[PDB]
Image 1: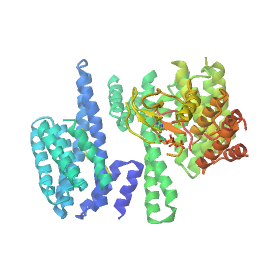
Image 2: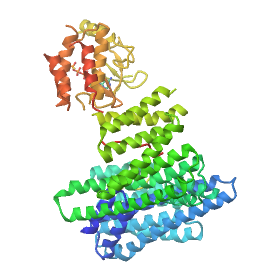
Image 3: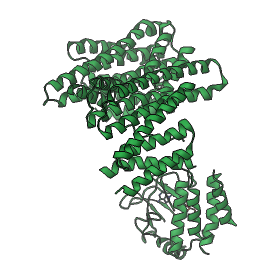
Image 4: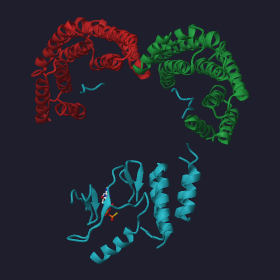
Length: 219
Length: 224
Length: 171
Ligand SMILES: Nc1ncnc2c1ncn2[C@@H]1O[C@H](COP(=O)(O)OP(=O)(O)OP(O)(O)=S)[C@@H](O)[C@H]1O
């Protein structure tokens, strides 16, 4: 388990590129990531996209406020696509490993749910990055990606299991933001928040239910 | 020309400095005189691209010490440290090459010369903290030399309460205690430096205070 | 938004209880003794320590006091131990003899016969908190076996402690 240990280490240093890069390898083996290597690949790519998505949210904002300058807006736009290209390049690198290696090897309900949800998000990030017709195709790719997860876990996992909420949290975040349809968003979370409360891991569960609660009062 | 400064700012709002440093050294190669705030761009652009590698190096090494009770992990933890070492060495040699080649030689203004020479002495010190063998010793002197040249120039022309001169004496002192392990010389430099500023302390006063508090807080650390 | 993760009288305690007079407060719900302790206790004021927020006489005599939310002395180092010695020292200076409690507000401000009688019990409280510089132990032993302004000076000497250096800020 050298790659995992190296990734555990690249996390401690906060060098996230090496996190994913040595995590890609164990996925490339055709093996089924364990409950730990799942999380290590999860944080590995989350921090790599959080950075670019965080840079994009800044450069995009500047590009809006630069109505004055003419050539300055050119560079601001030029850099933005440079981040999106960096953002897209990492996303394609994760989805590809997903479809090729993880989901095909998946056997457990949590395994399939985790990887399709991972597929779902890595299409929601692409959606925001996407500008036009790409948005339609990629979001359409996004909706299918999550939906397979949601119908898997409606019955093939306990009502309180964290991914069931994790699938509920982000699937909904795709619902409101990308589809611009709060109605489906609040419906998904409310159903999801309700079924857990009736069924009310506990400390883990309540960590994200607060985000489930805040979403409901958000949209 | 002016576009490069805009891109560097655009890389310090996205908080991605590897491009900010890369754009800044590109301005350096022009060989002209970095403006008052264009120079500051170069410092923070490079100050952050290094700080990220140093702390990454710090934890990795600390794990190497803590992981003395194993072999494979220490080999990899040592191997990963050598990776952060090498990355840091490259960044060091990149900044210094600009300073000695383009910036220091054209450092016409006294404030600029002390700034760069301190920065050269500074980015030498980072090299020393990681360097172990005789390379450390070679780096130790060049940190000392560059620290000293700025130190002297600051006295000759620069006020004793300027942020750079204070930051120079705070940094130089950190070299004494950390790289050299001479807290007697550390506190003498730190104490004398802030003591002189207090004598002439009376926006201009605020910045000096932030370093001075760093100066005084450093002293209390070293005394006990 | 946000996605999944990575990796009036209110409540009662005693008499004492919570309150709501101009905000959540504590209500200090025999009568002759209760009034006497109210008079001595009500003296404290005009400080960052021992602050109140109201009072009550009927239909149930009580005192409304400011609330506190933090790791109280028992509920929970030197950053407050200075405050406790100072607050008791200052109150002793104003000639209030307690001869007898410490609650944290914002988790940072710890809020609280002769003066030495309060000194004897404070040494015990300090000892439990510490169980580190030797001066702390010596001060506690001396109190159990001086003048509170002397104890405050004793903390000042205990303030010698203040890892790793720190270079010019990254800016
Ligand atoms: N203003 C306040 N803010 C927050 N908590 C308070 C406040 N006043 C009282 N309390 C709480 O209410 C509890 C009531 O107990 P105390 O009044 O401190 O002591 P007691 O239970 O009356 O017993 P003794 O023997 O008199 S110390 C305290 O321990 C605090 O936890």
